[PDB]
Image 1: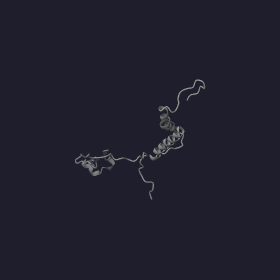
Image 2 (image 1 turned 30 degrees about the vertical axis):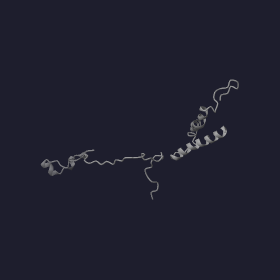
Image 3 (image 1 turned 60 degrees about the vertical axis):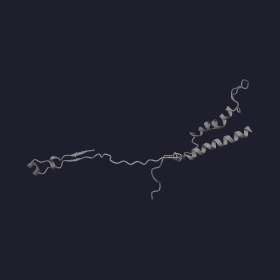
Image 4 (image 1 turned 45 degrees about the horizontal axis):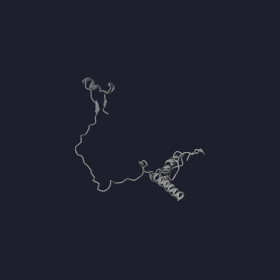
Length: 68
Length: 67
């Protein structure tokens, strides 16, 4: 269920932002100056809501030495 | 801007030299008008301020087709 829930929300969130840009006349472009904005869009709707609800882990691992 | 023009000695007719008269001096001015009547067009909204399009592009000032 979590994997499906991630699929749905990530898909609608990015689309919902592209429409706004394309509906103001300023559609997104592959200019390498606009692509990076996706860092905030994805981290905003799906990812952060996951952390506040406890669904997604975060922190550091002492034996594998990798972060979450 | 105001302008002033003054004749030079080469343009004064010989008769005016005898009579000692200078003419054709010209000046130019512009007058500034006061305000008398003013008209207002008020509008009272009831439900919602009129919405506007989301077209955030700069408004073009002319039409491309000109023939």
